[PDB]
Each structure stands twice: as C-alpha cells, then as structure tokens.
Length: 198
Image (cartoon, rainbow, N blue to C red):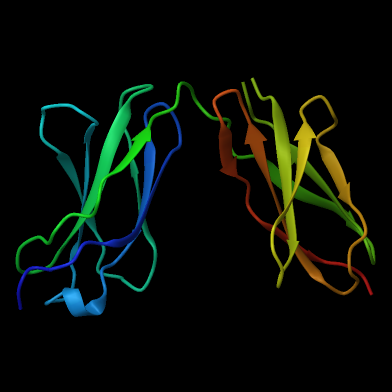
C-alpha cells in the first residue's frame, strides 16, 4: 500500500458566480490507487500569482461516481488555476493538469421553481417563478425520458408560462428551466417528470 500514482480523471471546472467555482472530477483508475482512497485535495490559486496553491480537503470514500466541490470566497473577475489530487492512508498522489477558469463579474440568477399546469396526449403546460431581484430571459429544457435535451430560448417580457406541443402520447417527458442574466446562466430548476395522455 502506497500513495496514489495517478491524477484524478475527467476534470471539469465552471464558475458559478463572482466568488465561486464548481469543480467536478472522477477518481483515477483502480490500478493507480494502491490503497482505498480517503478523499481528494482541490487546489486553487490566482493564475500567475507567486503565492503557492491553496488546497481544500474533500473527504470522499464513496467512488464510482462523479465528485464535485464548490470553491467559494474567491475574488471577482479573476482567473484561477485549478488542480485536484487523490489521497489514501499513505500519502497524497500526483495532481491533475491545470484548468484555468475565470470568476464571473456578477451574481447569477437563482434557480427557478417549475410546476405543472396541464397535460394532454400531445402537449404539456408549465409555470415557473422568479424569486429574483435583473433577469434577462429564460430557457426551457425538455426531453423524452429516453431521449436528448431540447432547448426553447425565451424572453423575460413574456408571461412565465409555456406549452410544449407536438409530443408523443403515453410518453414521459422531463422538463426544467434556467434563468439568464448579463453575467451568465443560472443554476437549473428541479426536473419535472410527467407522462402525456394516451
């Protein structure tokens, strides 16, 4: 049993506001653990800064999943380099490659709240809400359970209601809404599932 010899895989970073960055990753292959993993360290620093990396400890014994961690308390509109390491009972393993990501210039809108209105054999009607302070528009996301996500871009000036048309009958669709801002796209709402009538 030794320290891991491989970096985490499938690293993905995305800034979710002026102060926060969402980091996703997967574990290294089983052949590079050398001892069951106890967790990870997520490293971050300002891109060119001479200061060293700051590491956040993320405990994750559960594996076979996509791990994610929300860095917070960051600086507005600045670029950071992000890495992730793995560790076990023995020492820490090697870090992943750097992903450089910039924080946003402002706060994103809150995730909307979606609710079902009605459903027919070929249509589904949906309401949503703001709980916002300035929103610039929305996007409605829908799919059939077995299919791929389709997108309906929308304007904030309209009524916050929409009716999907031309749908298959006796088919379960999933629906959710995202809000839009000058600074970017907010988190998604919860996914509404409903089946069309026969």
